[PDB]
Image 1 (cartoon, rainbow, N blue to C red):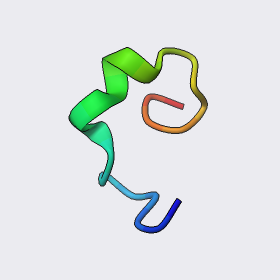
Image 2: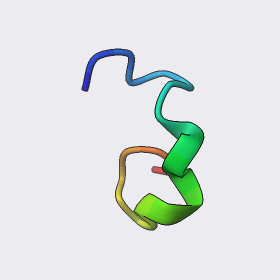
Image 3: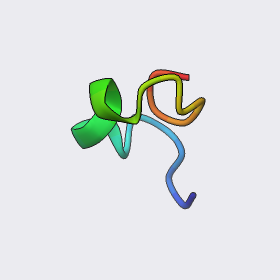
Length: 23
């Protein structure tokens, strides 16, 4: 959660529709 900004993009394409990274 913390640093919901560009932080956590290390696994964006991964999260997939995780509404967290790529949203």
